[PDB]
Amino acid sequence: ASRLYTLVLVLQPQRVLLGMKKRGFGAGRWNGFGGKVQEGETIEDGARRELQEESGLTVDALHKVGQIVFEFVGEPELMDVHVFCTDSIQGTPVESDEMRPCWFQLDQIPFKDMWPDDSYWFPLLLQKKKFHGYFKFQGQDTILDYTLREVDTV
Ligand SMILES: CSc1nc2ncnc(N)c2[nH]1
Image (tube, rainbow, N blue to C red; front, side, top):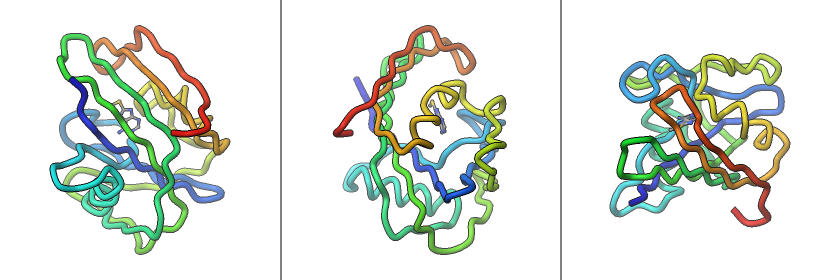
């Protein structure tokens, strides 16, 4: 009972693109781009598709940087999230129905208005380390348990 999702971070040398989620799950937080993988597409295709849909951007290349499993108390399906990052964007980001994009300098990442797991694994992403994580949440605000480690192969 796991379900595949994607998370894409646009990471340039001095800044990162995040999206203010307007509707639904994680609304009011600055999020990476992504969502559910569909039937008939690879995990990487799903990542490119969601990034395009949410921000208008396409990219030259995506790099797999991590995998995180989320469990929510009361929810039968685990979320199995494949995390990608990219520097090679094509186009300029624009607002979608779902998300309002905005750049943040790496020393002004708005951690207090992000999912609380981001405080744990973002540093690993910023150091170009590959990682495996697990987070158990109670609702959207409380982490009950977690594990996190560096890997060679994502
Ligand atoms: C579902 S738990 C979760 N953590 C996240 N961090 C950053 N961006 C997201 N969309 C995230 N979702």
